């Protein structure tokens, strides 16, 4: 299904982004700058995927209870972008001394 395709893309992208961010602190700044831009692009893709999932859940899941479950999961996934990407990235660029 489309929904499953987005979920898998989200999880794989999040994993890749986290791995690049974990490598970044060991890179000289010029290369690091390039790596972080890639992480930032992936962060955007993650938000993009969340948007696509919201729409697809809204369109394809009619059961009110099962919709609420999906919607809770997506809300936790948004928080995960914040905890796993945004916060660590921000900490690296602001307090990476």
Image (spheres, rainbow, N blue to C red):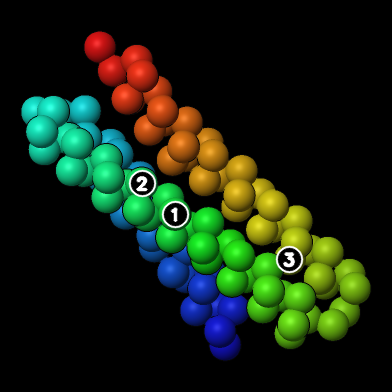
- At 69% across and 57% down in the image, what residue appears? 73
Q: Position of residue 72 (x, y in %)?
A: 75, 56
User: Could you say which is closer to the camera, residue 76 or residue 50?
Assistant: 50
Count the marks: how many? 3
The residue nearer to you, when weighing 44 against 60, is 44
Q: Relative to 21, say whether 53 is above or below.
A: below
The residue where tag 3 is placed is 70
Mark 2: secondary structure:
helix
Q: Position of residue 21 (x, y in %)?
A: 30, 39
The residue singled out by tag 1 in the image is: 44
Instruction: Please indicate, yes or no, whether residue 50 appears anywhere in the rendered image.
Output: yes
Disc 2 target residue: 40
- The Cα atoms of the two marked residues, 3 and 1, are separated by 21 Å
> The residue tagged with tag 1: helix, strand or loop?
helix
- Callout 3 crowding tier (Cα within 10 Å): few <14, some 14–19, many ≥20: some
The answer to whether residue 19 is seen in the rendering is: no
Label 1 and label 2: CA atoms lie apart by 6 Å
Q: Position of residue 14 (x, y in %)?
A: 42, 54
In the image, is residue 51 above or below residue 87? below
Which one is nearer the viewer's eye here, 4 or 89?
89
Please, is residue 32 above or below residue 81 in the view? Answer: above
Of badges 3 and 1, nearer the viewer stands: 1
Earlier sequence position, callout 3 versus callout 1: 1
Left or right position of 68 against 17: right
Q: Residue sitting at 74 percent across and 85 percent down?
A: 60
**Labels 1 and 2 touching (C-beta < 8 A):** yes
For residue 46, side relative to residue 68 (left or right)? left
Label of residue 4 in the image: none
SS label for mark 3: helix
């Amino acid at each position: 299904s489309l929904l499953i395709s987005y979920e898998s893309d989200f999880k794989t992208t999040l994993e890749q982004a986290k791995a690049s961010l974990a490598e970044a602190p060991s890179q000289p700044l010029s290369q690091r700058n390039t790596t972080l831009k890639h992480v930032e692009q992936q962060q955007d893709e993650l938000f993009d995927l969340l948007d696509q999932m919201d729409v697809e859940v809204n369109n394809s899941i009619g059961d009110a209870s099962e919709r609420a479950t999906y919607k809770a999961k997506l809300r936790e996934w948004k928080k995960t972008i914040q905890s796993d990407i945004k916060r660590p990235l921000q900490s690296l660029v602001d307090s990476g001394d």
